[PDB]
Image 1: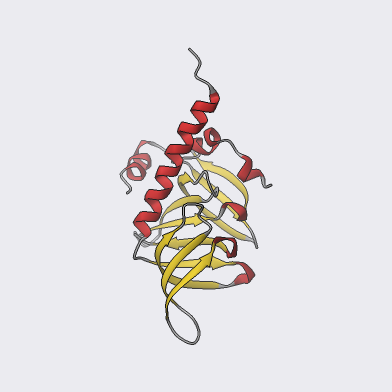
Image 2: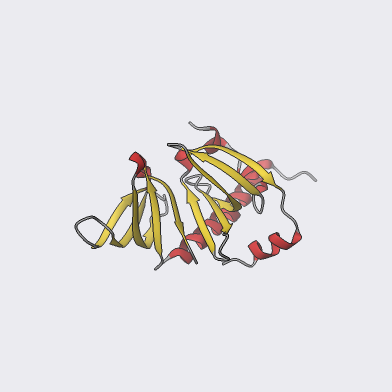
Length: 85
Length: 86
């Protein structure tokens, strides 16, 4: 029998999401390089995001005047992020 | 809203383990293997096996995604490497 597409979609949503959370959890404590809007790059250690993925919580944020202990980066300012496991 | 953010979860799911080229805001370009797409933000996660033998993981923010184009379907070997990840 054909399963409702709503059910199929929601199950695929759960699998995609679980994989995404796993990818973020593997990034905890690594240095990541953020590509920002306005052509800028910044580096920081990753701590967490919120579940809406609206903010990244980071530590050891590099700046021209020196390393900052903690910061919050808005995901709306970010284009991409990369790190090396 | 953007084309990429409107895609069904079942469509996002078919990109997994395929090699893809992503064009994003401000002329940023990426190529890599799809690990997943976050259904909340539409962030796409790519794995790269780099020239020096190391491995990177890259997320491109869903709001910044412009186009996504499949380049390679993959094979059993790469699929197993990617499955063993995390």
